[PDB]
Amino acid sequence: STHTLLGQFFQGWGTWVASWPLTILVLSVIPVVALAAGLVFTELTTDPVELWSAPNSQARSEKAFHDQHFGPFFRTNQVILTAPNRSSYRYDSLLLGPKNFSGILDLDLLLELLELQERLRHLQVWSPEAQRNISLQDICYAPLNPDNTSLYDCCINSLLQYFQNNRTLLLLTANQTLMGQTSQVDWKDHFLYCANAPLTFKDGTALALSCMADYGAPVFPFLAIGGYKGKDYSEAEALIMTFSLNNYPAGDPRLAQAKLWEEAFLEEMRAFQRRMAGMFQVTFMAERSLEDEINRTTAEDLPIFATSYIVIFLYISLALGSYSSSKATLGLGGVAVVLGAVMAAMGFFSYLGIRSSLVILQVVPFLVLSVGADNIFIFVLEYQRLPRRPGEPREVHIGRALGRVAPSMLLCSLSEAICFFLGALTPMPAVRTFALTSGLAVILDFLLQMSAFVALLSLDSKRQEASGEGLLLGFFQKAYAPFLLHWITRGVVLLLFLALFGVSLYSMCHISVGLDQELALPKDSYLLDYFLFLNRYFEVGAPVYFVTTLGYNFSSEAGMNAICSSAGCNNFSFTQKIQYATEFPEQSYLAIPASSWVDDFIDWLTPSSCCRLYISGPNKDKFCPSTVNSLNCLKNCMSITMGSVRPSVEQFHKYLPWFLNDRPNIKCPKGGLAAYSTSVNLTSDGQVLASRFMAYHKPLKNSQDYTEALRAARELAANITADLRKVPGTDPAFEVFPYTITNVFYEQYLTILPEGLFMLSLCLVPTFAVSCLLLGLDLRSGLLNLLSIVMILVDTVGFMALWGISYNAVSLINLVSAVGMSVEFVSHITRSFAISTKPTWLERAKEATISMGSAVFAGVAMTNLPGILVLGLAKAQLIQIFFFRLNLLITLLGLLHGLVFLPVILSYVGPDVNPALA
Ligand SMILES: *[C@@H]1O[C@H](CO)[C@@H](O[C@@H]2O[C@H](CO)[C@@H](O[C@@H]3O[C@H](CO)[C@@H](O)[C@H](O)[C@H]3NC(C)=O)[C@H](O)[C@H]2NC(C)=O)[C@H](O)[C@H]1NC(C)=O
Ligand SMILES: *[C@@H]1O[C@H](CO)[C@@H](O[C@@H]2O[C@H](CO)[C@@H](O[C@@H]3O[C@H](CO)[C@@H](O)[C@H](O)[C@H]3NC(C)=O)[C@H](O)[C@H]2NC(C)=O)[C@H](O)[C@H]1NC(C)=O
Ligand SMILES: CCCCCCCCCCCCO[C@@H]1O[C@H](CO)[C@@H](O[C@H]2O[C@H](CO)[C@@H](O)[C@H](O)[C@H]2O)[C@H](O)[C@H]1O
Ligand SMILES: *[C@@H]1O[C@H](CO)[C@@H](O[C@@H]2O[C@H](CO)[C@@H](O)[C@H](O)[C@H]2NC(C)=O)[C@H](O)[C@H]1NC(C)=O
Ligand SMILES: CC(C)CCC[C@@H](C)[C@H]1CC[C@H]2[C@@H]3CC=C4C[C@@H](O)CC[C@]4(C)[C@H]3CC[C@]12C
Ligand SMILES: CC(C)CCC[C@@H](C)[C@H]1CC[C@H]2[C@@H]3CC=C4C[C@@H](O)CC[C@]4(C)[C@H]3CC[C@]12C
Ligand SMILES: CC(C)CCC[C@@H](C)[C@H]1CC[C@H]2[C@@H]3CC=C4C[C@@H](O)CC[C@]4(C)[C@H]3CC[C@]12C
Ligand SMILES: CC(C)CCC[C@@H](C)[C@H]1CC[C@H]2[C@@H]3CC=C4C[C@@H](O)CC[C@]4(C)[C@H]3CC[C@]12C
Ligand SMILES: *[C@@H]1O[C@H](CO)[C@@H](O)[C@H](O)[C@H]1NC(C)=O
Ligand SMILES: *[C@@H]1O[C@H](CO)[C@@H](O)[C@H](O)[C@H]1NC(C)=O
Ligand SMILES: *[C@@H]1O[C@H](CO)[C@@H](O)[C@H](O)[C@H]1NC(C)=O
Ligand SMILES: *[C@@H]1O[C@H](CO)[C@@H](O)[C@H](O)[C@H]1NC(C)=O
Ligand SMILES: *[C@@H]1O[C@H](CO)[C@@H](O)[C@H](O)[C@H]1NC(C)=O
Ligand SMILES: *[C@@H]1O[C@H](CO)[C@@H](O)[C@H](O)[C@H]1NC(C)=O
Ligand SMILES: *[C@@H]1O[C@H](CO)[C@@H](O)[C@H](O)[C@H]1NC(C)=O
């Protein structure tokens, strides 16, 4: 038979290893030390948040195209101020009637915010790598002037940009006698005017102030104030101040300069928070802030987690005693064989240049320990329970006791390694390396404890020469087994577990898919207050870019008519569809309509002294800008007296680069480089390669909102690209896709549910087939522990839905490690039933419960409890939610099915009594 060959081979190998104890022990730990010595050579940790995105997916290929053709998305540094204990007040405007003002909108707070903003603009950091102070101008994102980049050209959005950050303009006052009403027009009137019409160059009040920021572009009200509802901007309860910086690829030396400045920004806002405790209530965030708040507690929690090894050392050599009136070296050997394998499997990957993560250094050594000492108890308890035959050496006895139990050990370890390796097909790189390291650690643990631990046990066995049945074996399990096999409980348990399975089957349909970003940070984190204020007070989400890939013409009148929204444009166009989709912002997750450069280019070509050509001179026809008050510019770019003015193909190639460099002013606010300078890529001749259109999501709170917004945006872009291909001239493969800064993270949840069912169902096939081959499990009890594993998975999914654990890529690998761990709870009990010889099924189930049930409870259920309970106090919600709540719920469910349900079900439909003398 296939079973008896393997057991007959393991009996020879163990008795050979026990005859050379010192040689096999020293010769095995040498490769373990050689593998674990690579923890210093190329041990590198991948700190960014690109450990959470598949690099060969569609969402990362769209990011590569947008980064190639337009440059990467800018970094963000935000502060959200609130005045909690300030009362609102009434104010009567000269143009808007009575209007109530919130407590935050006051001069006494706006002046303090102006002082803080002007101090942040002059910050400087001493760069160690490049010997020079880093100023804000060198790394700020300036849309209107990227070449010179003076200190006042940086993009800084706030409410004080309406007044251009001038303290004298903020305190300005005028007396307007409108309609026979002498009313003091103040800054609040100008703020009310700029909130309704942000693209204003002269205010429509008595004080004729401007309305646009000092860097040139107009600022919209949803980037300055927040917390309103509708269009009453005077009731705003929050103030926003955003600093945006240039983003570079990771190899660039400017990235270290840009991240160096944000540390000084965070220190300055911490000083502002401490200095203004009784006036404001600030919450802040830098672009580097989420990257270092995630892996901040990796080196802080390891010494707390290292006491699990001491507890598992103390648990062995107290439950393995022969206490009459201690096996302390066996516990040290069990700890060293588990500790050696983890360091060897972790350091082998460092040689190959595979970068580790935070989860590898936090759950790997305390999850391998929970399934690494599992075979040690099953070997040592079988060594002491098998009595020595008369006149035989200790080596043959150790070989016989090893050969009787080791195929179940090989089956459990190989099922563990198969489930970890098969579960490493997830696209996310943080979970792939964790599964690969856990699989290699489990395989090295199985090799180490079958070659070195047997030699250590043979060495310890000799020692007892120089220097009752216990209590757990017979004094409890011979007074619990009649309880469980009483004929009233034997029917009650059989329907109670069935009702539990049915209730979990109903309750697993209320599960939620997706991992919130609030559940990744430590509990005493400052970013949680920022995420609370962001979800409560903002009125728009992240920006959306509807990128158009190369292939569209853009130069024909048939091409422009499918994009524009003005007069003489086709119905259901690009901008028309994006305009329509924001009228129902619950189906489509858009809040602001798309701003199209083609419409502003068509409006800019209308002859209103905004595009003019020289009549004659030294410069005949090159360009007359808007800032020229001369008599030689009486010639429009386009002609006059047509409806739906569309430029020719020659005129489109000529007038377009002048439009994308024109700076808006009082005599020409029609458009230019304030918004569309970086939204269009031009070729060498002047042909448009690719463009992009800007729109804003609605506020996305949870992680399902991000997935629904991404799916709705991709569906709307699919409708737009379907309609755009019918225009004559555009070639196939032209597509319009929506690009957002957070689509790489949340694109996995579109199709993680079919991926989870396939990968989980693919692990049951090499758990039942291999169990029927390495063991004597033929067919009746072969598909019974599979039923136990399916019940364990369904009950775990139901309780995971009930507790409030979302189903994501982190929890999916824990379920795959549970299907490889539940074989350990049921294969030992089922195999002991199969080799039983008793008259009736009830006594066979009683013998199976007494013999291996006590060993399974004392070495498989109490061995992983120190390794799992230590993670419950872990400082990070991801480790404390997915690797503690899930694993604790699997060990209790796995113990409760493999020790109360499997013996009861085996006394009804168990396999027949084979003689089995071979
Ligand atoms: C409009 O699109 C153009 C075409 O993509 C952009 O020009 C591209 O800029 C890329 C970055 O400079 C180039 O990639 C580089 O290619 C060289 C040569 O192979 C490599 O050594 C570099 O490593 C590689 N850059 C990286 C970091 O991958 C493209 O080759 C280049 N393509 C063309 C046609 O010139 C324009 O940048 C874009 N317009 C603007 C101003 O953004
Ligand atoms: C975007 O659409 C434009 C309008 O459909 C295209 O412009 C057309 O390009 C044609 C060449 O491919 C021009 O044909 C030439 O015109 C001259 C002068 O009238 C004639 O001799 C011929 O018809 C032809 N050249 C030859 C063979 O001598 C069209 O005149 C021109 N149409 C317009 C309105 O100007 C663009 O080509 C298209 N852009 C792209 C991406 O190709
Ligand atoms: C293995 C576990 C570790 C991996 C888990 C990773 C969790 C998910 C990581 C999300 C990372 C990106 O996180 C996202 O960053 C952007 C940076 O623009 C923030 O967005 C910020 O900038 C945009 C645009 O400038 C503003 O509109 C926004 O209000 C502001 O918060 C998002 O609010 C944040 O959600
Ligand atoms: C802030 O605004 C004030 C007032 O507009 C600016 O001061 C003016 O400067 C011009 C140019 O020299 C003078 O002609 C005006 O008479 C000044 N007005 C007053 C009342 O002082 C001031 O320059 C602005 N500050 C900045 C930094 O732009
Ligand atoms: C053929 C002659 C030389 C007899 C001696 C052969 C012995 C010394 C060789 C043959 C197979 C070898 C074993 C093969 C596998 C392992 C697992 C590894 O993780 C530790 C070393 C260990 C345990 C080797 C020890 C040395 C070994 C036992
Ligand atoms: C009982 C537990 C801690 C056993 C695990 C020990 C090893 C595998 C763990 C514990 C502490 C960890 C180290 C903590 C800090 C660093 C510094 C970093 O720049 C490189 C990785 C490195 C060197 C880690 C490597 C892995 C590590 C050495
Ligand atoms: C980094 C990327 C781009 C390269 C490919 C990495 C992944 C997909 C590759 C590299 C090594 C591969 C693994 C190599 C070994 C095994 C064990 C086998 O029993 C199942 C497949 C499995 C688990 C492979 C899965 C796919 C795998 C993990
Ligand atoms: C079935 C086995 C594992 C027995 C243990 C089940 C226990 C640990 C599980 C099952 C149901 C769970 C509870 C379900 C509901 C809540 C409400 C929540 O706001 C706090 C946690 C709490 C109170 C859970 C605590 C843990 C819990 C009690
Ligand atoms: C402003 O708020 C107060 C709160 O009571 C409300 O009574 C008042 O009517 C509001 N002002 C206007 C113009 O409605
Ligand atoms: C700027 O750099 C110079 C030379 O390194 C240094 O003396 C000066 O102190 C730096 N500026 C600040 C703000 O310290
Ligand atoms: C930008 O501006 C400064 C000051 O006008 C000028 O001297 C410098 O040459 C310019 N540099 C670039 C790269 O545009
Ligand atoms: C008009 O307003 C000014 C400044 O606000 C004030 O000083 C002056 O008294 C007012 N003039 C009249 C005629 O009331
Ligand atoms: C606002 O005032 C209340 C009442 O005095 C006080 O309890 C609270 O701490 C104050 N908050 C801040 C941020 O000053
Ligand atoms: C939609 O198209 C039709 C036919 O091209 C046109 O008559 C109508 O004016 C367009 N838009 C509407 C419905 O106003
Ligand atoms: C595109 O597909 C259908 C057909 O035009 C349309 O009903 C649907 O509303 C469009 N998609 C979106 C996101 O509106």
Image (cartoon, rainbow, N blue to C red):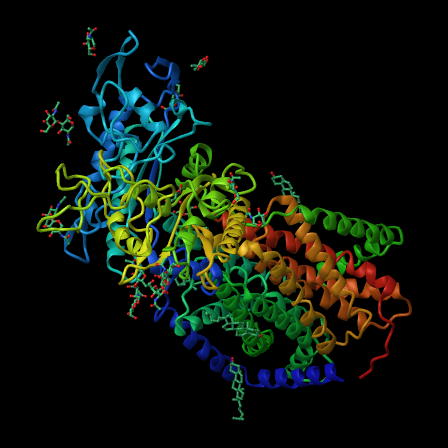
Q: Furthest-front residue in view?
A: 641
Question: Residue lying farthest top?
Answer: 180
Residue 35 in the image: x percent, y percent? 43, 75
Q: Quadrant of the N terminus?
A: bottom right
Question: Of all residues shown, which one is farthest toward the left?
Answer: 618
Which quarter of the picture shows residue 13?
bottom right
Answer with the quarter of the image where residue 42 lies: bottom left
The image shows residue 123, relative to residue 224, as above or below, that is below
Does residue 198 lie above or below 514 as drawn? Answer: above
Q: Nearer the viewer, residue 468 or 248?
A: 248
x, y percent for residue 33 = 42, 75
Residue 263 at x, y = what percent? 28, 46
The quadrant where residue 787 appears: bottom right
Q: Is 174 on the left-hand or right-hand side of 24? A: left
Q: Quadrant of the C terminus?
A: bottom right
> Is 65 left or right of 394, judged from the image as shown?
left
Q: Position of residue 173 (x, y in %)?
A: 22, 17
